[PDB]
Length: 270
Image (cartoon, rainbow, N blue to C red):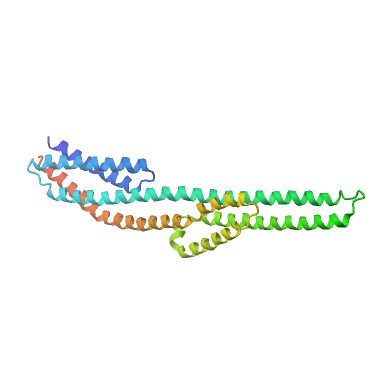
């Protein structure tokens, strides 16, 4: 009978609205893909059902339309959460890299300070080995001057490790929520923190290491892009939000029209 159709029509709509529901969420690619497919398939089942009912003297032209508007609207939304999903993936990858790069710089900085600290200790320890008919003053004065230079490089490195950690934390602090509220602040904030890190970068002793820090710096300098990613993400998130409210009225009209047709079927059935 035609009654078995109304049950499927209700069912297709329950799964459609359910797929459309899950799609607009979608945390991972897998869910997005799976739900988009399901939505498409359900829309196809509804179209086939409507065409079956229509050739039963039943009128489906109001539902055919609404359902078509809804499929168009969800296509767009599906696309948008698709791009957004990508962005949120790029943000993670890029940020992952920047902290790693900042952390390597900090580690390289600590390494350098340790070398100077170990040297100064040796030199100073050397001043006490002087007692050996070795005219102190000549040596003592030179060793002392050497320890002061070592210690001076320690500060320079400790200041490098710090500049690097500052930036690492700032990046670890981005999250859209705050990139939205205080955006220009967080930005000009990192520009200095990075322009500083760069300044101190070009001040490393052995250019061999001053080189690795140079490559790492180029990676951390992409923070400006990681910012662009977060922006686009919010330009879409608000967008997707707007459409999510239009759905209410659309979905209200659609389901309400299914009910009306299902009735015309459970009433004409007797």
